[PDB]
Protein backbone atom coordinates (compact mmCIF):
# COMPACT_ATOMS: atom_id res chain seq x y z
CA UNK A 1 0.00 0.00 0.00
CA UNK A 2 2.89 2.38 0.88
CA UNK A 3 1.63 5.85 1.77
CA UNK A 4 -2.08 5.71 0.89
CA UNK A 5 -3.79 9.07 0.14
CA UNK A 6 -7.35 10.34 0.75
CA UNK A 7 -9.03 11.96 -2.28
CA UNK A 8 -12.26 13.99 -2.38
CA UNK A 9 -13.16 13.57 -6.07
CA UNK A 10 -15.68 16.43 -6.19
CA UNK A 11 -18.01 17.52 -8.99
CA UNK A 12 -16.36 20.98 -9.39
CA UNK A 13 -13.29 20.78 -7.06
CA UNK A 14 -11.07 17.91 -5.88
CA UNK A 15 -8.88 17.70 -2.76
CA UNK A 16 -6.09 15.35 -1.62
CA UNK A 17 -4.69 14.62 1.85
CA UNK A 18 -2.41 12.24 3.76
CA UNK A 19 -1.92 11.16 7.40
CA UNK A 20 1.57 11.70 8.90
CA UNK A 21 2.93 12.47 12.41
CA UNK A 22 -0.52 11.73 13.92
CA UNK A 23 -2.36 14.43 11.97
CA UNK A 24 -3.88 15.16 8.53
CA UNK A 25 -1.97 17.32 6.03
CA UNK A 26 -4.03 18.59 3.06
CA UNK A 27 -1.57 18.79 0.15
CA UNK A 28 -1.20 21.97 -1.92
CA UNK A 29 -0.88 21.58 -5.72
CA UNK A 30 2.02 23.20 -7.65
CA UNK A 31 0.04 26.52 -7.82
CA UNK A 32 -0.23 26.50 -3.98
CA UNK A 33 -3.97 25.64 -3.80
CA UNK A 34 -5.32 22.95 -1.42
CA UNK A 35 -8.29 22.41 -3.78
CA UNK A 36 -7.98 21.67 -7.50
CA UNK A 37 -10.82 22.20 -10.05
CA UNK A 38 -12.14 18.95 -11.58
CA UNK A 39 -11.53 20.49 -15.03
CA UNK A 40 -9.98 19.12 -18.24
CA UNK A 41 -9.40 21.16 -21.42
CA UNK A 42 -7.35 21.25 -24.64
CA UNK A 43 -5.80 24.42 -26.13
CA UNK A 44 -5.85 25.50 -29.82
CA UNK A 45 -2.46 23.67 -29.76
CA UNK A 46 -2.04 20.01 -28.65
CA UNK A 47 -1.58 20.92 -24.94
CA UNK A 48 -3.79 19.10 -22.38
CA UNK A 49 -4.62 21.06 -19.20
CA UNK A 50 -5.89 19.70 -15.85
CA UNK A 51 -6.92 21.73 -12.78
CA UNK A 52 -6.53 25.51 -12.34
CA UNK A 53 -4.99 25.94 -15.84
CA UNK A 54 -8.06 24.24 -17.41
CA UNK A 55 -10.62 26.37 -15.48
CA UNK A 56 -8.82 29.69 -16.22
CA UNK A 57 -9.11 29.21 -20.03
CA UNK A 58 -12.83 28.21 -19.74
CA UNK A 59 -13.85 31.68 -21.04
CA UNK A 60 -11.77 31.48 -24.27
CA UNK A 61 -12.62 27.77 -24.88
CA UNK A 62 -16.27 27.46 -23.72
CA UNK A 63 -17.32 24.36 -25.74
CA UNK A 64 -14.26 22.06 -25.22
CA UNK A 65 -13.60 22.51 -21.48
CA UNK A 66 -14.86 19.37 -19.69
CA UNK A 67 -16.19 19.51 -16.12
CA UNK A 68 -18.95 17.88 -14.00
CA UNK A 69 -17.94 14.44 -15.38
CA UNK A 70 -19.01 13.09 -11.96
CA UNK A 71 -22.66 13.84 -12.94
CA UNK A 72 -22.34 11.29 -15.80
CA UNK A 73 -19.87 8.75 -14.33
CA UNK A 74 -21.28 5.20 -14.08
CA UNK A 75 -24.72 6.06 -15.56
CA UNK A 76 -26.52 4.80 -18.68
CA UNK A 77 -27.69 7.02 -21.57
CA UNK A 78 -31.41 6.37 -20.80
CA UNK A 79 -30.89 7.49 -17.14
CA UNK A 80 -33.23 10.50 -16.51
CA UNK A 81 -30.41 12.24 -14.58
CA UNK A 82 -28.07 12.24 -17.62
CA UNK A 83 -30.75 13.61 -20.00
CA UNK A 84 -31.43 16.50 -17.56
CA UNK A 85 -27.75 17.43 -17.03
CA UNK A 86 -26.67 17.49 -20.74
CA UNK A 87 -28.98 20.54 -21.21
CA UNK A 88 -26.96 22.46 -18.54
CA UNK A 89 -23.54 21.44 -19.98
CA UNK A 90 -21.86 23.49 -22.79
CA UNK A 91 -19.71 20.61 -24.16
CA UNK A 92 -21.32 17.91 -26.34
CA UNK A 93 -22.38 14.56 -24.82
CA UNK A 94 -23.36 11.62 -27.05
CA UNK A 95 -24.46 7.96 -26.74
CA UNK A 96 -21.92 5.17 -27.31
CA UNK A 97 -22.70 1.55 -26.28
CA UNK A 98 -25.82 2.86 -24.42
CA UNK A 99 -23.58 5.06 -22.20
CA UNK A 100 -22.69 8.81 -22.15
CA UNK A 101 -19.37 9.93 -23.73
CA UNK A 102 -17.77 13.41 -23.80
CA UNK A 103 -16.67 14.69 -27.25
CA UNK A 104 -14.03 17.50 -27.39
CA UNK A 105 -11.44 19.05 -29.76
CA UNK A 106 -7.71 18.37 -29.15
CA UNK A 107 -6.32 21.02 -31.52
CA UNK A 108 -6.21 21.78 -35.25
CA UNK A 109 -9.88 20.80 -35.70
CA UNK A 110 -9.32 17.23 -34.41
CA UNK A 111 -12.06 15.70 -32.20
CA UNK A 112 -11.87 12.93 -29.56
CA UNK A 113 -14.47 11.12 -27.39
CA UNK A 114 -13.66 10.28 -23.73
CA UNK A 115 -15.61 8.20 -21.19
CA UNK A 116 -16.48 10.02 -17.90
CA UNK A 117 -14.03 7.59 -16.22
CA UNK A 118 -11.14 8.84 -18.41
CA UNK A 119 -11.89 12.49 -17.52
CA UNK A 120 -12.05 11.61 -13.79
CA UNK A 121 -8.88 9.51 -14.26
CA UNK A 122 -7.06 12.61 -15.61
CA UNK A 123 -8.19 14.61 -12.54
CA UNK A 124 -7.12 11.72 -10.27
CA UNK A 125 -3.70 11.60 -11.98
CA UNK A 126 -3.29 15.32 -11.14
CA UNK A 127 -4.18 14.68 -7.45
CA UNK A 128 -1.81 11.67 -7.52
CA UNK A 129 1.04 13.80 -8.98
CA UNK A 130 0.25 16.58 -6.44
CA UNK A 131 0.64 14.02 -3.60
CA UNK A 132 3.79 12.48 -5.16
CA UNK A 133 5.46 15.93 -5.26
CA UNK A 134 4.78 16.52 -1.52
CA UNK A 135 5.77 12.99 -0.37
CA UNK A 136 8.75 12.60 -2.75
CA UNK A 137 7.80 9.06 -3.83
CA UNK A 138 5.28 7.18 -6.02
CA UNK A 139 1.70 6.69 -4.71
CA UNK A 140 -0.10 3.45 -5.70
CA UNK A 141 -3.13 3.30 -3.34
CA UNK A 142 -5.91 5.73 -2.31
CA UNK A 143 -9.19 6.16 -0.41
CA UNK A 144 -11.72 7.88 -2.72
CA UNK A 145 -15.01 9.44 -1.58
CA UNK A 146 -18.34 9.29 -3.46
CA UNK A 147 -21.88 10.62 -2.70
CA UNK A 148 -23.99 8.38 -0.42
CA UNK A 149 -26.64 7.93 -3.16
CA UNK A 150 -24.09 6.46 -5.67
CA UNK A 151 -25.02 2.91 -6.80
CA UNK A 152 -22.69 -0.07 -7.53
CA UNK A 153 -22.08 1.01 -11.17
CA UNK A 154 -21.12 4.57 -10.10
CA UNK A 155 -18.90 3.23 -7.27
CA UNK A 156 -17.16 0.79 -9.69
CA UNK A 157 -16.73 3.52 -12.36
CA UNK A 158 -14.95 5.67 -9.73
CA UNK A 159 -12.64 2.68 -9.03
CA UNK A 160 -12.04 2.27 -12.81
CA UNK A 161 -11.06 5.98 -13.04
CA UNK A 162 -8.52 5.27 -10.26
CA UNK A 163 -7.16 2.19 -12.09
CA UNK A 164 -6.54 4.22 -15.30
CA UNK A 165 -4.66 6.83 -13.19
CA UNK A 166 -2.58 3.98 -11.66
CA UNK A 167 -4.35 4.07 -8.28
CA UNK A 168 -5.59 0.99 -6.41
CA UNK A 169 -8.75 2.46 -4.82
CA UNK A 170 -8.68 0.37 -1.59
CA UNK A 171 -11.96 1.72 -0.16
CA UNK A 172 -14.91 3.69 -1.51
CA UNK A 173 -16.32 5.80 1.34
CA UNK A 174 -19.43 8.00 1.44
CA UNK A 175 -18.78 11.79 1.51
CA UNK A 176 -20.97 12.48 4.61
CA UNK A 177 -19.31 9.59 6.50
CA UNK A 178 -15.86 11.01 5.62
CA UNK A 179 -16.96 14.44 6.94
CA UNK A 180 -18.21 12.74 10.15
CA UNK A 181 -14.82 11.00 10.52
CA UNK A 182 -13.03 14.36 10.06
CA UNK A 183 -14.86 15.73 13.14
CA UNK A 184 -13.93 12.61 15.17
CA UNK A 185 -17.62 11.66 15.58
CA UNK A 186 -16.53 7.98 15.33
CA UNK A 187 -14.96 8.45 18.82
CA UNK A 188 -18.43 9.29 20.28
CA UNK A 189 -20.00 6.70 22.65
CA UNK A 190 -23.26 4.77 22.12
CA UNK A 191 -26.00 5.54 19.58
CA UNK A 192 -26.31 9.06 18.09
CA UNK A 193 -28.02 10.66 15.06
CA UNK A 194 -25.94 12.93 12.76
CA UNK A 195 -27.19 15.45 10.18
CA UNK A 196 -24.68 16.25 7.40
CA UNK A 197 -25.44 19.43 5.42
CA UNK A 198 -23.23 19.62 2.30
CA UNK A 199 -23.59 22.79 0.19
CA UNK A 200 -20.96 22.85 -2.60
CA UNK A 201 -20.47 25.06 -5.66
CA UNK A 202 -23.18 23.36 -7.75
CA UNK A 203 -24.67 20.60 -5.51
CA UNK A 204 -26.55 20.33 -2.20
CA UNK A 205 -26.66 17.05 -0.22
CA UNK A 206 -28.35 16.32 3.11
CA UNK A 207 -27.65 12.98 4.84
CA UNK A 208 -28.99 11.46 8.07
CA UNK A 209 -26.35 9.11 9.54
CA UNK A 210 -26.53 6.97 12.64
CA UNK A 211 -23.45 6.00 14.61
CA UNK A 212 -23.40 2.77 16.67
CA UNK A 213 -20.28 1.56 18.54
CA UNK A 214 -18.07 3.85 16.38
CA UNK A 215 -19.60 2.63 13.08
CA UNK A 216 -21.83 4.71 10.78
CA UNK A 217 -24.85 3.98 8.56
CA UNK A 218 -26.55 6.24 5.98
CA UNK A 219 -30.28 6.08 6.84
CA UNK A 220 -31.67 8.58 4.28
CA UNK A 221 -30.45 11.19 1.78
CA UNK A 222 -31.94 14.23 0.00
CA UNK A 223 -31.00 17.69 -1.32
CA UNK A 224 -30.80 19.48 -4.68
CA UNK A 225 -28.38 18.42 -7.44
CA UNK A 226 -28.39 21.86 -9.15
CA UNK A 227 -28.22 24.17 -6.08
CA UNK A 228 -24.89 25.59 -4.90
CA UNK A 229 -22.58 28.59 -4.42
CA UNK A 230 -22.64 29.41 -8.16
CA UNK A 231 -26.42 30.05 -8.03
CA UNK A 232 -25.77 32.67 -5.30
CA UNK A 233 -23.15 34.31 -7.57
CA UNK A 234 -25.64 34.37 -10.49
CA UNK A 235 -28.23 36.34 -8.46
CA UNK A 236 -25.50 38.89 -7.59
CA UNK A 237 -24.43 39.01 -11.27
CA UNK A 238 -28.04 39.59 -12.41
CA UNK A 239 -28.41 42.39 -9.82
CA UNK A 240 -25.26 44.35 -10.77
CA UNK A 241 -25.72 43.92 -14.58
CA UNK A 242 -29.25 45.39 -14.22
CA UNK A 243 -27.83 48.21 -12.05
CA UNK A 244 -25.15 49.04 -14.66
CA UNK A 245 -27.72 49.35 -17.50
CA UNK A 246 -29.97 51.48 -15.25
CA UNK A 247 -27.17 53.98 -14.46
CA UNK A 248 -25.06 54.15 -17.67
CA UNK A 249 -27.59 52.85 -20.23
CA UNK A 250 -25.21 50.08 -21.39
CA UNK A 251 -26.13 46.38 -21.77
CA UNK A 252 -23.03 44.35 -20.83
CA UNK A 253 -24.56 40.87 -21.43
CA UNK A 254 -23.10 40.31 -24.94
CA UNK A 255 -19.53 41.21 -23.82
CA UNK A 256 -18.22 37.86 -22.52
CA UNK A 257 -14.87 39.36 -21.38
CA UNK A 258 -16.39 42.08 -19.13
CA UNK A 259 -18.90 39.61 -17.59
CA UNK A 260 -16.02 37.31 -16.48
CA UNK A 261 -14.22 40.30 -14.88
CA UNK A 262 -17.39 40.90 -12.79
CA UNK A 263 -17.84 37.19 -11.82
CA UNK A 264 -14.24 37.20 -10.47
CA UNK A 265 -14.94 40.17 -8.14
CA UNK A 266 -18.42 38.85 -7.18
CA UNK A 267 -16.83 35.53 -6.09
CA UNK A 268 -14.20 37.43 -4.04
CA UNK A 269 -16.85 39.70 -2.47
CA UNK A 270 -19.11 36.72 -1.60
CA UNK A 271 -16.20 35.10 0.32
CA UNK A 272 -15.39 38.45 2.03
CA UNK A 273 -19.05 38.81 3.17
CA UNK A 274 -18.70 35.57 5.21
CA UNK A 275 -16.57 37.60 7.68
CA UNK A 276 -17.38 41.28 6.78
CA UNK A 277 -20.66 43.25 6.32
CA UNK A 278 -19.74 45.04 3.05
CA UNK A 279 -17.35 44.61 0.10
CA UNK A 280 -16.38 47.18 -2.58
CA UNK A 281 -16.28 45.83 -6.16
CA UNK A 282 -14.07 48.07 -8.33
CA UNK A 283 -13.15 47.22 -11.97
CA UNK A 284 -11.21 49.83 -13.98
CA UNK A 285 -11.78 49.73 -17.80
CA UNK A 286 -14.77 47.41 -17.26
CA UNK A 287 -16.72 48.03 -20.50
CA UNK A 288 -15.97 50.50 -23.35
CA UNK A 289 -13.19 52.01 -21.18
CA UNK A 290 -15.70 52.90 -18.43
CA UNK A 291 -15.20 51.94 -14.76
CA UNK A 292 -17.43 49.90 -12.42
CA UNK A 293 -17.75 50.99 -8.77
CA UNK A 294 -20.49 49.45 -6.57
CA UNK A 295 -20.75 47.89 -3.09
CA UNK A 296 -22.29 44.55 -2.07
CA UNK A 297 -23.60 44.41 1.53
CA UNK A 298 -24.19 41.15 3.42
CA UNK A 299 -27.83 42.29 3.82
CA UNK A 300 -28.24 42.76 0.04
CA UNK A 301 -26.43 39.48 -0.76
CA UNK A 302 -28.84 37.75 1.69
CA UNK A 303 -31.87 39.58 0.22
CA UNK A 304 -30.98 38.49 -3.35
CA UNK A 305 -30.63 34.81 -2.30
CA UNK A 306 -33.13 34.51 0.59
CA UNK A 307 -35.54 32.16 -1.27
CA UNK A 308 -32.63 29.88 -2.30
CA UNK A 309 -31.25 29.85 1.28
CA UNK A 310 -34.65 28.89 2.80
CA UNK A 311 -35.16 26.13 0.17
CA UNK A 312 -32.23 24.19 1.77
CA UNK A 313 -34.43 23.50 4.86
CA UNK A 314 -37.09 21.47 2.96
CA UNK A 315 -34.62 18.59 2.20
CA UNK A 316 -33.47 18.67 5.87
CA UNK A 317 -37.12 18.24 6.98
CA UNK A 318 -37.68 15.48 4.36
CA UNK A 319 -34.68 13.33 5.45
CA UNK A 320 -35.92 13.57 9.08
CA UNK A 321 -39.35 12.30 7.90
CA UNK A 322 -37.81 9.41 5.90
CA UNK A 323 -35.60 8.58 8.94
CA UNK A 324 -38.72 8.77 11.19
CA UNK A 325 -36.95 11.30 13.48
CA UNK A 326 -37.82 14.63 15.12
CA UNK A 327 -35.61 17.77 15.22
CA UNK A 328 -34.71 17.06 18.88
CA UNK A 329 -33.38 13.54 18.04
CA UNK A 330 -30.33 15.06 16.22
CA UNK A 331 -27.17 14.91 18.39
CA UNK A 332 -24.58 16.25 15.89
CA UNK A 333 -24.74 18.70 12.95
CA UNK A 334 -21.88 18.81 10.41
CA UNK A 335 -21.58 21.62 7.83
CA UNK A 336 -19.52 20.82 4.70
CA UNK A 337 -18.79 22.87 1.54
CA UNK A 338 -17.62 26.48 1.13
CA UNK A 339 -21.19 27.87 0.97
CA UNK A 340 -21.77 26.80 4.63
CA UNK A 341 -19.40 29.66 5.62
CA UNK A 342 -22.30 32.03 4.75
CA UNK A 343 -23.66 33.34 8.12
CA UNK A 344 -27.31 33.22 6.94
CA UNK A 345 -27.02 29.50 6.04
CA UNK A 346 -25.61 28.73 9.53
CA UNK A 347 -28.36 30.76 11.28
CA UNK A 348 -31.13 28.98 9.29
CA UNK A 349 -29.71 25.55 10.23
CA UNK A 350 -29.19 26.66 13.86
CA UNK A 351 -32.78 28.01 14.11
CA UNK A 352 -34.35 24.91 12.48
CA UNK A 353 -32.75 22.82 15.28
CA UNK A 354 -33.96 25.24 18.02
CA UNK A 355 -30.58 26.91 18.68
CA UNK A 356 -28.27 23.85 18.52
CA UNK A 357 -24.68 24.71 17.49
CA UNK A 358 -23.13 22.98 14.42
CA UNK A 359 -19.64 21.44 14.63
CA UNK A 360 -16.76 23.83 13.77
CA UNK A 361 -12.95 23.58 13.49
CA UNK A 362 -12.37 22.07 10.02
CA UNK A 363 -12.10 23.88 6.66
CA UNK A 364 -15.49 22.89 5.13
CA UNK A 365 -13.95 22.79 1.62
CA UNK A 366 -11.48 20.14 2.90
CA UNK A 367 -13.51 18.21 5.54
CA UNK A 368 -14.25 15.26 3.19
CA UNK A 369 -10.62 14.86 2.03
CA UNK A 370 -9.59 15.19 5.71
CA UNK A 371 -11.80 12.20 6.64
CA UNK A 372 -10.57 10.15 3.67
CA UNK A 373 -6.95 10.88 4.73
CA UNK A 374 -7.71 9.57 8.27
CA UNK A 375 -9.03 6.30 6.75
CA UNK A 376 -5.90 6.24 4.54
CA UNK A 377 -3.84 6.77 7.74
CA UNK A 378 -5.40 3.59 9.19
CA UNK A 379 -4.60 1.57 6.02
CA UNK A 380 -1.00 2.88 5.60
Image: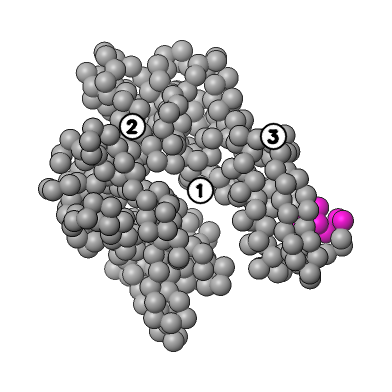
Residue 277's label in the rendered image is: 3
Question: Which of the two residues, 170 or 5, is positioned nearer the viewer here?
Answer: 5
Please name the residue shown 39% across and 77% down the image.
Answer: 47
Q: How many marks?
A: 3
**Helix, strand or loop status at disc 1:** loop
The residue carrying pointer 1 sits among few (fewer than 14), some (14 to 19) or many (20 or more) residues within 10 Å by Cα, namely some
Q: Quadrant of residue 103?
A: bottom left
Question: Which of the two residues, 200 or 48, is positioned nearer the viewer here?
Answer: 48
Q: CA distance from mark 1 to mark 3?
A: 24 Å
Please name the residue shown 38% across and 73% down the image.
Answer: 48
Query: What residue would you read off at disc 2?
Result: 182
Q: Are marks 2 and 1 in contact (CB under 8 Å)?
A: no
Question: Which of the two residues, 330 or 279, is positioned nearer the viewer here?
Answer: 279
Query: What residue would you read off at disc 1?
Result: 202
Disc 2 versus disc 1: nearer the observer:
2
Disc 2 versus disc 3: nearer the observer:
3
Q: Are marks 1 and 3 in contact (CB under 8 Å)?
A: no
Q: Is residue 12 magenta?
A: no
Of helix, strand and loop, which mostly describes the magenta segment? helix
Disc 1 versus disc 3: nearer the observer:
3
**Helix, strand or loop status at disc 2:** helix
Q: Is residue 161 left or right of residue 254?
A: left
Q: Quadrant of residue 167?
A: bottom left
Amino acid sequence: SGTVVGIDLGTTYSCVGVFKNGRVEIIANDQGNRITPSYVAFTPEGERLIGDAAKNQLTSNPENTVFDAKRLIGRTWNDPSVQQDIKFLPFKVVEKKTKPYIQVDIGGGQTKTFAPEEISAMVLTKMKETAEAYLGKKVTHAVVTVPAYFNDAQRQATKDAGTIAGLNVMRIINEPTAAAIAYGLDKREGEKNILVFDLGGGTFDVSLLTIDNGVFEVVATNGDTHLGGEDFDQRVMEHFIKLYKKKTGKDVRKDNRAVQKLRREVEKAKRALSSQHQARIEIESFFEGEDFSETLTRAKFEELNMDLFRSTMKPVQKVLEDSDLKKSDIDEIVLVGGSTRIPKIQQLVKEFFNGKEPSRGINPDEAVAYGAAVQAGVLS
